[PDB]
Length: 111
Length: 97
Length: 111
Length: 97
Image (cartoon, rainbow over all chains, first blue to last red; front, side, top):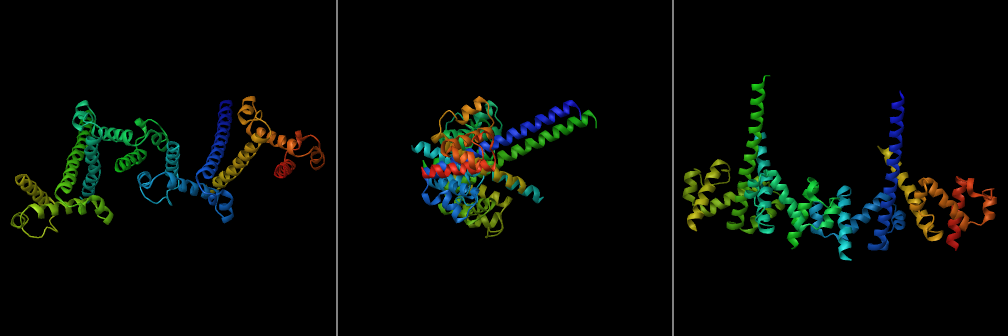
């Protein structure tokens, strides 16, 4: 292990920790966005407190809020296009992120 | 030989999309993007197909849908399953139109 | 492997891919004709959407449309002569291509 | 990969805690302690969070609770489970306020 190896290992470690921190900030922003969307566009029965009392994981809460927002704003034909199917119960993921971006678009144009 | 038979079936399957896009694009976008003139300008079959798909997206699918679903405003480099989603969305927009 | 072998291999590969492209063009014309014939001469119940909903392969849709067109246009005597049998349920193929060519001629002379 | 999944679960937990602390601190203390301006002044994220927690304690928790529960009047070096106790006391105080 030479000086250049030491420097490159240190730089790689620092960059890895920085990337982890950026991921933390991204997750915090995602949680904030989900909270705002649930408060603004969805009913109080879908609140994080009541869902947790019913016993659902936080990721399950986020995806349920996203699916409800997609059904509320994004119409069924666009759903059938982007997700290639009508049902959203098994489309959580990158396609779900795309659909909720479409829902944000729909609410922006609705206002 | 059944491998080549399934290859020919795949040819039919993609061929369907090839002609359908042309048929709807001729009536929706313009005559400037006709396959013959595009070939004359020197565009391969796949390039014509993807360019017509992108023009269909730019006509039906709105720009906010482009920059949010596809994560980029420019459809110039989004080709793939995202492009499939966008062209399906354009089919929806023309269906409801 | 010498340079002449390199050139002949490269040319063979390029020609194979060009043949693939020619197949694409021809087959696209085939499907275009199938769609136009189904829209113009056959009922809405035989549409590709409803057939796919009923769960039939694309090749099955094309051959069903071709058989219906042959029965609609080509006379039964011509079917019994060219295809050697009255039933078309097992005549999909090159004989079916000849039958649909005869049907195209029939509609052209009908107009 | 479930080890990384649980790591990400803890990451979500601390991110939500940070978000809640920031949201209440912005409306309670001042705009001078905003995350952007603190980062510009050159404080790490954890340092920003602990400074905001200490300011929350200094705002809601009365000084005697600090000099007895934390055994020191200065919250400058009490960080830890005692700091968690103090910020929970601050939450109680703002709830009753």
